[PDB]
Length: 129
Image (cartoon, rainbow, N blue to C red; front, side):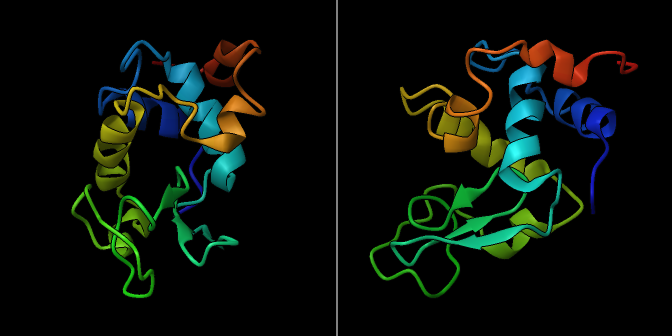
């Protein structure tokens, strides 16, 4: 499902992302835009075998089990297949545990490279919440 700008916002807010470890809803929506263009079906290999899963480009290497990443752990404890659904609950709860790895939201590249050091609140601007 290709989410809206504001319905993923209202979706991630309702799941308690707005100011989670102190990152505004504007950080998540911004990240989400450049990870997967608001696509729950987005799937990306890496150079180290492992594959990026869904809205937040969550990493099979450290997080979900996808059945073909040898040196893996799924500390999030989910089949990657879940992070591809129209449902973002597994994608959010997994993200709460990543953002809380004393790394903030830097764990995600397309946020510390395209989002950090910009007006992130423009990304949820003019939306009803």
